Amino acid sequence: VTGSGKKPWRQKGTGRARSGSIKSPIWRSGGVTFAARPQDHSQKVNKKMYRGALKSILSELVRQDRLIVVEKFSVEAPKTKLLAQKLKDMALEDVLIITGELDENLFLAARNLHKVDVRDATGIDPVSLIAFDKVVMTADAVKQVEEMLA
Amino acid sequence: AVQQNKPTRSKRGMRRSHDALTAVTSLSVDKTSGEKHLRHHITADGYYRGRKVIAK
Amino acid sequence: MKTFTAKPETVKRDWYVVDATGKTLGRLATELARRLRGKHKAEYTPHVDTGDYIIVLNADKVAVTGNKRTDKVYYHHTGHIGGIKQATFEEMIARRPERVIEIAVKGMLPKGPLGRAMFRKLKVYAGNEHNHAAQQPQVLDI
Amino acid sequence: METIAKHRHARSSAQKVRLVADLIRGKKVSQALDILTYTNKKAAVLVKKVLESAIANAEHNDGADIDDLKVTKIFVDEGPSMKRIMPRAKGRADRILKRTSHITVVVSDR
RNA sequence: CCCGGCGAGGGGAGUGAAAAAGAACCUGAAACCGUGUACGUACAAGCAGUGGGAGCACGCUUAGGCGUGUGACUGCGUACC
RNA sequence: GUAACGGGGCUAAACCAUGCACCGAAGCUGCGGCAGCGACGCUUAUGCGUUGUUGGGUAGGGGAGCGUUCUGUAAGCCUGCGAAGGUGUGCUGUGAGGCAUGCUGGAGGUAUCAGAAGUGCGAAUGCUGACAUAAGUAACGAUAAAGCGGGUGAAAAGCCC
């Protein structure tokens, strides 16, 4: 805290409590007793534990019928209107789409839809698999996941 | 020299029970001009007992 | 249900006359205090005065056992530095005979505003005559 | 119908003004004016002006008759205090409060 | 427009959804200080409450004798860290 | 200042012996309720039928919770048909608390289950602001001194002549 280290007043003689610094945390405008510092909140996750969690999540999705497998999933042009119409036919509104190859046309179409996310087979994370109501995975995408999880 | 305890608002009110002012019982009326005035005092217009004392 | 409580504005008080000639001071006083407090009534309530009015006659003829007639001393302080004054039982009887019974009964009654109120119902006379005939006191052989 | 007149931020402590106010509480306006005229207090001048203003408000705004008016309510409230410094001996400083007050007068035809 | 010292400060009028948003201006707590109403209080002694408890006022009620405020009198009772 | 029964008073209301009653505590019993620990019915994804027993507490150890701000759940849900905050009332739990609602207020608030803490104040001759008390009391700063007429002004002991 900006200020001088001078004693505000002498130790004895005045009828006031002891003071040694104007920056004492007791005083107004003083420093914070345990002032915070920037810190890293990341935690370690064992490789096997992380892989085990993904397998449990995927199994639960199949149990709850929240996982849908399709032969292919693509759009003709990078237009949001086409993708939105496609999802209406399949009765999907909040879905996560995983594809083996991240087609640029599909990626651009889904950009403006905040309830739709397009991810690569290697880009799946545990939170995403749970956050979205439904998960759509292509047949080739299903194959890729198997070796990653083994 | 100084108090050892803070007196209460009740004690403050009790001490002030004798501080009330007293209003004049009544005002005299001049026999000639008819204006009210303090008894044994000249009126604002300079009258006293209907004699028209100096009013310069 | 709640226990019954006497009401100060609906309590019945009677009048009695007692002759103190030849009666022991202390034993007479206890009975007077008991009746002034209303302890003899089934409607007795500690915070209500349910006693009776008592008239005491011949207060100057009370009796005391032993040598108390000349040895019992009544002390009282006037509030000044000298203050301490005393009078024997014989002196009190000669000067203020009524005070002898009055003092004894007062010490036997509860202390406080209610106890003071109880004492107001006791009438003590040195002679054998009283002027409370209008109240029709009933003879009490106590 | 009751008419209100106020004098806010008057230069006088509420305690001093309250002494005069209690003299005219509940009195007829004509009688109240006479009492204030012959009261040798500074607060009397302040209170009289408020009472006169209340009477004037009744005629102009409410169309009332003065002969029927009386001081139904009157009270004095503490106002903001002005802080000042008064030097004392041996270099000590003291705080001086210049207290003010709000004067309210209500006149009604009741 | 009115009172006032061609004041200060107010009362109307008008503006605005709101002026108890009027510039000492969003919301406007507490200490502290007032006005009004109900009840208690001028023969009574102490950590001021607690248990009991009359009377009075008031809101109820198919008189339902309960609720709310006050607390004469009485048992016990010497704050906190 | 009685002052060597607490008091009044007591010739028993004192003392010794014997006997029978009664008063007397948060002790014991009766009635209702809560919780801890044991064994039992192998009951039970465990609560009981029960069943005994325990429950003063500083330093201190162990166990289980309330509420506050913030992140996800939440582009959800509540809200100008009135949010947060302020102020009353009623109801409710063993407690920290919770729920509903009148008035004020005039735009934000947030379930559930998880996550992170600048997370709870009466005291430290604590810190800052506000306001009390003494009190309408002391004091108004050299005891060189003022009186009157007129003027001005809403108002003159203090200004002008």
Image (tube, coloured by chain):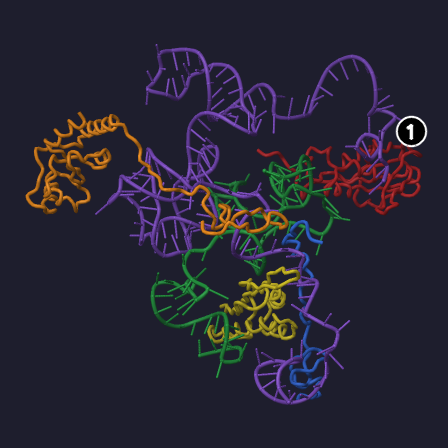
Chain colours: A orange, B blue, C red, D yellow, E green, F purple
| Viewer can see residue C100 | yes
Which residue lies at the image location 61% right of the left edge and 34% below the top edge? C3
Q: Is residue C69 left or right of residue E74?
A: right
Which residue lies at the image location 7% right of the left edge and 45% below the top edge? A77
**Res F23 quadrant in image:** top right
* Residue placed furthest toward the front: A5
Pick the residue in front: E60 or E1.
E1
Q: Quadrant of the N terminus of chain C?
A: top right
Q: Position of residue A31 (x, y in %)?
A: 46, 47
Q: Residues within 10 Å of mark 1 (few under 14, many from 20)?
A: few
Pick the residue in front: A89 or E59.
A89
Which residue lies at the image location 19% right of the left edge and 34% below the top edge? A124
| Viewer can see residue B52 | no
The chain to which mark 1 is attached is C
Q: Quadrant of the C terminus of chain C?
A: top right
Residue position for label 1: C66
In the rendered view, would you say B26 is above or below A140?
below
Tell me the element at label 1.
Answer: loop
**Res B39 quadrant in image:** bottom right
In the rendered view, would you say D36 is above or below C38?
below
Q: Is residue A42 left or right of residue A20?
A: left
Q: Position of residue B12 (x, y in %)?
A: 65, 56
Q: Position of residue F42 (x, y in %)?
A: 35, 12
Q: Position of residue F120 (x, y in %)?
A: 47, 41
Q: Is residue B4 left or right of residue D57?
A: right
* Residue placed furthest toward the left: A76
Which amino acid type is shown beneath numbered disc 1? Gly
Pick the residue in front: B46 or C119.
B46
